[PDB]
Amino acid sequence: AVQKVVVHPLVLLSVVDHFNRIGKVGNQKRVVGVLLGSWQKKVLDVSNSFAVPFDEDDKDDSVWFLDHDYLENMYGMFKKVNARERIVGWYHTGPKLHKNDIAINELMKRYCPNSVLVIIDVKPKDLGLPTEAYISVEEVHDDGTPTSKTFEHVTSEIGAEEAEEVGVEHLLRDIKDTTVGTLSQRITNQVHGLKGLNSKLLDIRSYLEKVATGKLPINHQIIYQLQDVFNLLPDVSLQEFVKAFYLKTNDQMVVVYLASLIRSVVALHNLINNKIANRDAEKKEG
Amino acid sequence: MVLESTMVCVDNSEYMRNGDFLPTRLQAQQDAVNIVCHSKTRSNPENNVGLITLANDCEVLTTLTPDTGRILSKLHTVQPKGKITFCTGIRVAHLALKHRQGKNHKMRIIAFVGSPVEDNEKDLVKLAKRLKKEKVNVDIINFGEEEVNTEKLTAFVNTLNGKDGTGSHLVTVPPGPSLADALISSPILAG
Amino acid sequence: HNMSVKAMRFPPKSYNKDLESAEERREREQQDLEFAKEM
Amino acid sequence: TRPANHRQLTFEEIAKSAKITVNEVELLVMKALSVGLVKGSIDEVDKRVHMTWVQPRVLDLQQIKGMKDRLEFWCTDVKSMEMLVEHQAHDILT
Amino acid sequence: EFLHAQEEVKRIQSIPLVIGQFLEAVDQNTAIVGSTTGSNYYVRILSTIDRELLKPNASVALHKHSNALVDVLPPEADSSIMMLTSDQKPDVMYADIGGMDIQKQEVREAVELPLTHFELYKQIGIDPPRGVLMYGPPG
Amino acid sequence: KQYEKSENDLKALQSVGQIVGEVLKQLTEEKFIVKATNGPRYVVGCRRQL
Amino acid sequence: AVDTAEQVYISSLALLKMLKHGRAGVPMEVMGLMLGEFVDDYTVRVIDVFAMPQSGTGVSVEAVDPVFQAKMLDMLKQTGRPEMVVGWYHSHPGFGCWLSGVDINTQQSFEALSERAVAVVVDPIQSVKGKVVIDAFRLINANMMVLGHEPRQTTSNLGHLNKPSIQALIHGLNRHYYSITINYRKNELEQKMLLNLHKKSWMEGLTLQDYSEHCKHNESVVKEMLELAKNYNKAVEEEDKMTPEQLAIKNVGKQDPKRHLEEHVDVLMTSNIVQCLAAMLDTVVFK
Ligand SMILES: Nc1ncnc2c1ncn2[C@@H]1O[C@H](COP(=O)(O)OP(=O)(O)OP(=O)(O)O)[C@@H](O)[C@H]1O
Ligand SMILES: [Zn+2]
């Protein structure tokens, strides 16, 4: 239903500072808060957020509290200072998908119809993007209990804004791999993207570990996609795909040959522009 | 005035479903809640009163507020039907008591039982010594009908005012459908 | 191409001062800016 | 059963395994394409069909060993090919 | 660091920008414009402008206090837009004019026939007319 | 009420005039180009809600 | 007294709050409140900023409702953690930064509460990347200006490091208020999680980029690159001629083939090589 999301650095830091301001609890706390923003053109947007007062105990871990007085009053304030701004969903700090995050969404679904969640990271280390968002469905299959409230991950990305890029680029001042030439693609996706294939490669290997040892659900709805992958594995070197390849490339290196061929003539013309500069400078200057 | 925050736990379980008490059980304990929040409110303007239940779905129907009109509106057509779950009533009380406005306030809860309980006394003695280690003073007032003589309740309040607590109370239900105001005339006079 | 880079970087020599703008014109800019600030 | 090497079969083999005549198997496989349990093409003159996609079925705890092993050396191709990019492309990015 | 300072200068562009018109340049990287306030000035440039987007009558951008070149503009006029083409073509056919065979075919030669078949005027080279005048009694 | 009627003018003397202009064309979403009934042509931005 | 070595520390979030709320209602002078720990006589560490909604239409600074900041002060008290109000701000939008006569009044209403309150001006237009422009201020007593006496008694080479702007020098600059050198507090906990997340492709370079139109676009550059090279066979030939400064001023009306050429050589080069190598890795990786 909703295509993808847009997340700002303001909300991105604006969870982490709250994790600091409850960071004096020491023992254990998750950061849970209310996510605010709009969505237009079936593109989700996230602009602002805050956090709800919240506690939890491990013994009888089916008890949670969201102060709706704080919710109504503070969102009334945010509506008052910005009527354009509104509710969009929620977020929890999300290390590993806590258990109450199946009916928190049911607790606050009366506010937003597509009451969406956001899982973030407070210990940032990965080779990907540590921002996650699911969506609520209660989809029905064809075996066992039908209507099952399973969250489903819609794709996610960090959105920019012309206002906030001044502050972001100001707060970097650290490293910036611009001059995007023949190098920046090699590292933004050719070095790094293979490691992007490494983790998704290793993930199904980790799921695979139930061979006779792991959890109880065997396959049913996992192996049609895997069987579809191994059926969908590409063509081997026999056909014209080789000769179209060879044939293909062979066309591209022509254009490479022309471009490199003109570049040397350009630099040689600059050398003549240099000779004229130094010669008619030696006898004239002295 | 004196620092507390009154947290009432209402009983919307499925054994609250007759007119044995004269107007309505719901209206009777409802107006009891009204006059005890007049007592706590008019004895202390700082005290706020919100309501929780200990049924299957322990919902915060009203957020903890010094208002009473939302409390009245939710107690209108509250639909007291569902399976009681008392063992999570302790956690859904105390965790909100950690959610309260200030820990300078006295941890005081009133708890309403008008249904048969299926708890273990081991479970409420783990939660009871949990309330000992958390220093929590709850006076439980029984309503409606009950397993006679509060089975596990005397042991619970005993394991609540035990170890120099000795100030917590357990008002049992008299099994006669009378006007409950004189039934609760003792804790409102002296806790 | 690279040899046409390596054997042509000689040129940059001789000339050695790129002045910012001036000194006395900077002082006169401070005086005229001081008069605009006084105005 | 047929691997991804060929997965290409003949109407003689279909006539054997279903023991039905030559002039019915085409009407069978057009029905199979109509249901969409299988996806492939039909050549008539060489009497062979190029089956590409099949309906995904279920399997026991034995085929997951095969998919495990096919996964396993598929990992080290990514390792080995990626290591050329790391080692050789090292001076382009520190 | 040169990439950092490279973007740093363009804060001067910003918003509160007034409009003049480019006239000519004295030298490399210093020029002469005419403000739409009416007066002309001897102004400085901004470095990152492609100078080959200037030509003659360029609409330029001027800083509201320092009064120097800022940015080049896509062209603008208010005298008229461009005859907006939807509710703008007066419903009038060529057949609505009767008895103007000389002048209709003649202005057809004068205007749109060099607009389309330019290579005949160039190829034979008969110097197609720049502007046309038409007159007579009214109506 | 006499302090109220004068209290209208207590803060009512703070509105500042608005230059009457005219839209020429539109460069970008935020880059606009106008000219008043006074003189020169300007480059201008708008409120983000209007 | 002070030593003009005050050194305000702020945050890594409040800058974002200032630019967002200062940018959303930008042509009106929006404002709000500042909220952080007040450390010693020299420094201050303002960790948080919440904004205040306006009073009505009109370019000014409106007023402050202590009902509203009394409540909002307590929302974080009963939810997050207690802090202290230290300063406040407004927004000269595209002006630069100074104190107006209206600004100095509402400042003067705040310094009487706490003597080390802070005036702050954000300018969310003239900032681009390295120029954020804030320059927090505070009043100086005009009584000592009547005394003819110099305040603020410099004991450290820390004050006169930034030269003041000429427009604030036209304004009350040094006769009614002073500047404060500020900086920022940050950590790798934030630096990594904003660097690693801002501009990230996912698997996009592991694609093929419109495989019919790649060679077609390659044609679509080379075709006019021919005639542009004919112009390079035009523009060299007026050397051994008039001086290159005239060959510098004279080339401001018509395009040159040189720079325009070496642009397109780069575009064809990096356009081709990425599609080549990225095309060839998948042959190994996928079967
Ligand atoms: N075929 C025609 N030839 C000449 N006149 C015609 C024809 N058909 C209609 N007319 C009339 O002649 C008039 C021509 O209008 P038009 O405005 O072009 O006149 P004009 O020559 O421009 O005179 P003026 O300059 O005074 O307007 C029209 O009002 C129309 O009524
Ligand atoms: Zn101001």
Image (cartoon, rainbow, N blue to C red):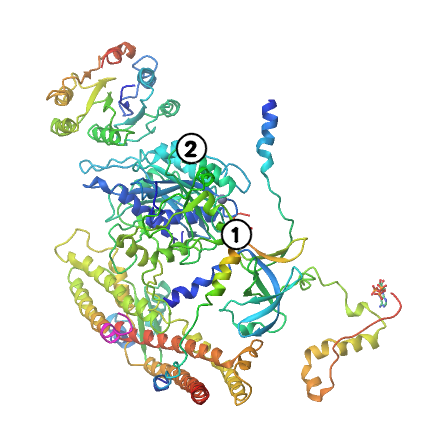
Image: E89 above or below B96: below
According to the image, label 1 marks what residue? C37
Q: Is mark 2 within 8 Å of ligand 2?
A: no
Q: Could you tell me which chain the residue with mark 2 belongs to?
A: G
Going by the picture, which residue comes out furthest to the right? E137
Q: Quadrant of the N terminus of chain B?
A: top left
In the displayed structure image, the side of residue B57 where residue G247 appears, left or right: right
Q: CA distance from mark 2 to mark 1?
A: 41 Å
* Residue at the image position 19 percent from the left and 41 percent from the top: A26
Disc 1 element: helix
In the displayed structure image, the side of residue G32 where residue E94 appears, left or right: right
According to the image, label 2 marks what residue? G68
- Where in the figure is residue A207, as x and y percent of width and height? 20, 57
State yes or no: residue D88 in magenta. yes
What stretch of residues is rendered in magenta?
D84-94
Residue E104 visible in the picture: yes
